[PDB]
Amino acid sequence: DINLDKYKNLTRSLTREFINLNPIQRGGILPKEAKKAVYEYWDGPPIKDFLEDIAKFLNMDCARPTHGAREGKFIVMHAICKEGDYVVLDKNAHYTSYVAAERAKLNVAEVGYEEEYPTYKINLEGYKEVIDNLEDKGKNVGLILLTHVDGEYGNLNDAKKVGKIAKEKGIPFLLNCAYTVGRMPVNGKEVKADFIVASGHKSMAASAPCGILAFSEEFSDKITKTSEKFPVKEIEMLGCTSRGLPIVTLMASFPHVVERVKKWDEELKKTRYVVDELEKIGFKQLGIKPKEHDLIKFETPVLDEIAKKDKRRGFFFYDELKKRGIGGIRAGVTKEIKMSVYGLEWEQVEYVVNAIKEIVESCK
Amino acid sequence: DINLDKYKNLTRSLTREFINLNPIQRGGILPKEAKKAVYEYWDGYSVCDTCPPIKDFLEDIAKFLNMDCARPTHGAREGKFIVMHAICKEGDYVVLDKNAHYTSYVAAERAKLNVAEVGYEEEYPTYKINLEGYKEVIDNLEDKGKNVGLILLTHVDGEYGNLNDAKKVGKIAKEKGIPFLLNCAYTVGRMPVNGKEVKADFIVASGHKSMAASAPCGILAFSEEFSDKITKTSEKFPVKEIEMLGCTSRGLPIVTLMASFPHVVERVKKWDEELKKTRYVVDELEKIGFKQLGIKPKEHDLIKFETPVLDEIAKKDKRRGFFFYDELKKRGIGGIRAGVTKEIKMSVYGLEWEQVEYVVNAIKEIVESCK
Amino acid sequence: KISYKDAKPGKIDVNEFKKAIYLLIEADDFLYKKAPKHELNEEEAKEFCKLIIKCQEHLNKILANFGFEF
Amino acid sequence: ISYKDAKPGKIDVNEFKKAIYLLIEADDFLYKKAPKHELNEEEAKEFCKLIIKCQEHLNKILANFGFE
């Protein structure tokens, strides 16, 4: 009644045979230490000390482990805000912010762009305005969210501004550092944030659902609110035992991460190398220039032209990348491509760039 | 300011050097197929929307429980909170058994719900739940009169490991038209379970506890009747499920859960052998002086022994009540709480018969040699 | 006799490698199912040493591409 | 050299774990040198060192079952 053959030859992937350009995976690649830890604990750890240390790493008062930035955002939205409260976020926000807001029965207010094409930079001051427009209508703002780096254009935002605004208005501030914590250094107190969500599998060299929620002492009682029936178990954490593979890989990759954030400018160097070298063949870097993050979005008219006549339609590029052992770009899309070379060896960066150049050169 | 040394030699565990008797870890041990699967997805590129057939796995797992639909979670915890948050209204009552897991109470408290407990049919030493009593608890609540949003039954409790005839509570639930959730954290993946046959509207399952998976990992199966509520999609994103926080469950746990699936569906057919190991352990250890608490005979691999002998020995021993632990560590056996002698809690599920023999004989020798 | 210093530039046979590490993963099972003594009988010893030896054959095939003859 | 000649013995867990760790370290080359996986002289020495150490440990394991 059930075909089990689809789970037998499951042991197959191009992880070792291909170069992965997908931005959502560059920062989540396990170092060998993490792999050894996986071998050790794939069914079976100084967690408290790790929480204190990850608290210091972000310059924050307290910290808890989650199943990603998703979970953390839902946690703060569910423990701090009351049903009906508004969440004011930027227009470049991740879908999980909106969805977590909707699960917490909260409303959403967006902040416009300082400029659209091709920068798509968020008008940070606009936040202030957007708040007042809500408070004049009598609405209550419960949370101010800012995606530190968005997953579309990879733009870095001066979080200290929105921090100042949030501090003035007295509204709690959540900084979405899913694309930040683990890549670049980040000071929670310096940007005046009350909550910080980090994605372990996206930027902290961990696997599985894995994340961190850092928060100030002010809200410590609310976030870590214990249960009535069980005075030891935290309610929002659903049981303060956070065990499994992801937390192990995270703790194991922690020294690798705290060391690689000190060498963020080298990864930036790789990024800008790719951008500068690709804009020669007809690519146009979208988002803020120059790049302050590894996530790059290119507008590529050339690829669309090649896919036009004729080849295998928009799926040509993908195919032409598979021939050269490169993946991570969505198949079929040619109007624009989204890529990142974070953590790639320089020889591999050169290989990728030269590969792309050869692709556009050979396919006319 | 931060010491990184504590994360250097993290690569150290007695997972291979010792026999773990911890019941919460017996059913979660990875088969070699799942280990190879872990290897193939080591880097962490397992985006399941690049990933094993997740949709087909949801259909197949739906069939495996004989349920309408199913969705991946991060454990039975998450599932309980899902159903309590999507189906019940703030202030409603959840009527669960007295042997319920703590995560049920905590999930109820996070969903802003109240809790009503169903009493026992017999306390010591059976600690069996009076299933009919559920009715008596609901009526008493309706005449008071609050409203009951959910009826929860832990299929097997994590304290005594007693199996319960869920069909009764399901029948009461259907008669009263109240949604019925069955907590199968200790059931699904060990023994065969039929969701429709027990008249359950929801079933939660733990991948890391009873489905040979690792990490936070679980399954939430549900009937069509509630599919519109559970899988309710969002406004801004008409494909992203609200309760799921986005139709994506990427990572190692789901990969292992899919890779261990044939092993699981093939090992539930050989459940009686594990029950045989369990009963062997009970019958053999009762000769020492251990008394099996819970329902006799055992219908689950989770055993709780009342151990007066260990107390007696601990009274006249140098290292006091830790001796047992120590005396188990010398012979390569772990999974028992250190400094606990009044009672022990163990499981030999998945162990080779030779290993079961080793455990029993080892314990016998512990009691015999320590007088 | 065989030294790593004598290694010449070559290509890694990915398939052979993953084969070897798979063999090792299968052999890793014995660490579990035979704990804590880890003592094998004749049959178990044969079955285990088969995995180990096959793994060594694969590793030798890998070393072959780097100027190592056998 | 045949597996059929294997005589009963004990699995050295430490040695096995060492071999595994070595193969895991060697697995890095599959990543940092993809997709061509061609090594230069120094890289070849570094990789073959890991592989050879691994086979050494495997031989130490086989020693406990009547081999040499």
Image (spheres, coloured by chain):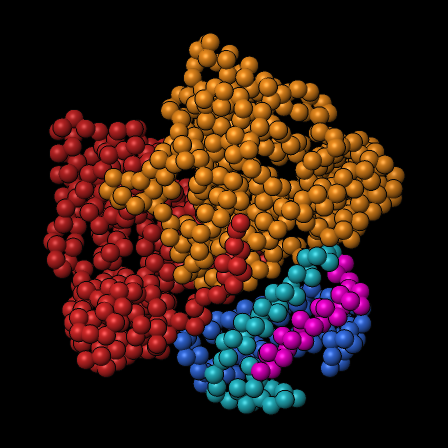
Chain colours: A red, B orange, C cyan, D blue
Nearer to the camera, C64 or B163 = B163
User: Quadrant of residue A296 in the image?
Assistant: bottom left
Q: Is residue D19 above or below residue B130?
A: below
The prevailing secondary structure element of the residues shown in magenta is helix
> Is any atom of residue B93 visible in this view?
no
Residue at (21%, 64%) from the top-left corner?
A336
Q: Where residue B41 appears, x then y in whole percent?
A: 47, 61
**Does A12 sit left or right of A162 as displayed?**
right
Quadrant of image for the C terminus of chain B: top right
> Is any atom of residue B112 visible in this view?
yes
Residue at (75%, 65%) from the top-left corner?
C44
Q: Is C65 part of what is drawn in magenta?
A: no
Nearer to the camera, A9 or B72 = A9
**Does B31 sit left or right of A85 as displayed?**
right
Residue at the extreme top of the image, as rendered: B143
Residue at (16%, 54%) from the top-left corner?
A121
**Does D49 sit left or right of B368 as displayed?**
left
Nearer to the camera, B243 or A309 = A309
User: Quadrant of residue A287 in the image?
Assistant: bottom left
User: Quadrant of residue B9 in the image?
Assistant: bottom right
Residue at (59%, 17%) from the top-left corner?
B133
Q: Where residue A76 appears, x then y in whole percent?
A: 35, 37
Q: Where residue D10 appears, x then y in whole percent?
A: 77, 66
Q: Is residue A57 above or below residue A321?
A: above
Q: Is residue B72 above or below residue A294?
A: above
Specify start and end residues of the magenta stretch as a single range.
C37-61
Q: Where residue B188 appears, x then y in whole percent?
A: 57, 41
